[PDB]
Structures are given as C-alpha cells and as structure tokens.
Length: 123
Length: 123
Figure 1 (cartoon, helix red, strand yellow):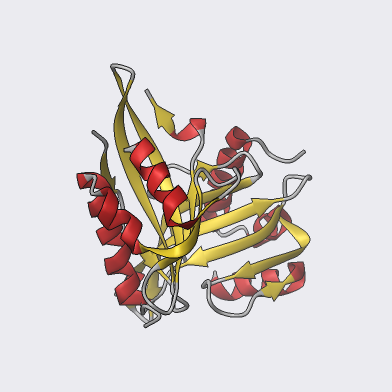
Figure 2 (tube, chains in turn blue, yellow):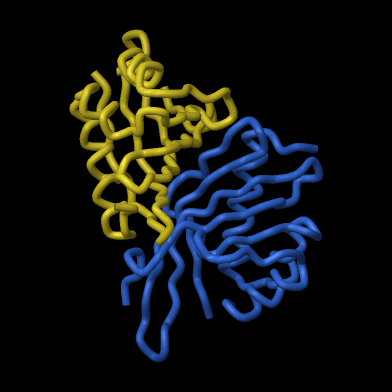
C-alpha cells in the first residue's frame, strides 16, 4: 500500500543499502516500471526501468551512506541526506546529496529528485 | 538575479541563521510576496507574506542549526538538512527536518517544502 511515514524511512534506508553494495537489479526493482529520475535535479529526467538501469549501471566501486535520518511525510514522500564516495580517475572524491522520493500505492519509487552540484563535490 | 548554486547555499544558510535568532521580519522578507509554504509537506499550503508571517510568529525560544551542507542545483533550487530544538510544554524536544526551496529571479523564496513528521521528533 501507500507506505506510511515509518515505512518510507525503511524503504529509503534500504535504497542506500542497495546503492552501497551495488546490486543494480535490486535497485531497479525498487522503482516503478515507468518511474522518472532527475539526477542531478535541473537536468532532463530519465524515464522507465530500462533507462534507469542504464543510469545506475553507468554510475556504479561506489560506497554510499546515510548522513542523517530519513525525513518522511504522510503522503508517501521522503527526503534523505547522504554521502557518496567514489574515486574519480585515480583521485578519490566525495559527493553530498539529498534525495527526494515519492512512492506509489505499491511501495515503489514513482519519482526521484537528487539535489547536488559541483558545490557539493570534494575531490 | 536567479541565484547560482553558490548563492543558493548562502541564502539557505542565512535563512537558518534567521530562524535561529528568531528575527521574524527578516525571515518574512526572504520570501516572495506571494510565496507558498508547505510545512509539513503533505498539509495544505499557506500563501503570501501575511499568512507566512503569522505562521512564523506562531511557530517562533527555538534554536535551529544546519546539520549538513546545503545541496544546491543550477536552476535556483536547494535542499538542506537541519535540526530544530524546542521545549514542548516544559519538556524539551528536537525535530529533524529537510527544507526544499525554489528561488525566483530576484533571489527570494518562491516556494518552500518542509519534510518531517512524528517519526522525526524526539521528545
């Protein structure tokens, strides 16, 4: 069903867990079949599981961790702060991001927006 | 002008500074005259400076602090994680919140959404 506030916290925490281990298939399955992703927020969105799988396969040796609690609403939405550690061309770097997600009545991510830019990168 | 990513970080950091000291008039002036606020996200929005001033005067002895860096995009938007400390009826409590803001071409907050619920309260 439409995830409650407590359920949204668990779903979003799980999402970061999946990104951390790099299980591309488990990540893609968390999204609705026609979900849209705007990463970073400001650029045109990618639509559907095929494009999303390509996005995550391309983006993912990356370690991600929640840097604060998941903020959840009562209308199936949530927002969370986290850090992504990568090694950009031999040189290691970190990226601070905030993801905003809206879930559907099946508990899947319907839309996702990622807030970050070069100001949040540390290389 | 439409704030750059670096400018959005400064504006949002300033906003928390104002909430922390409790300068209601300086806070209200940061919003556009017809801005909308959804706090908490999920409830109907308040529109305009009059209603917003009433909201902040009612809500504000409160101390707020950024708990992580401001995430900013290139389209005049940003998101930030912070904690609000209040003393609910003699008993002290904290609230973890994430604010998402969109600025206009004048550098004022056009819309603001606050993500939090009872799951983010510690009393």
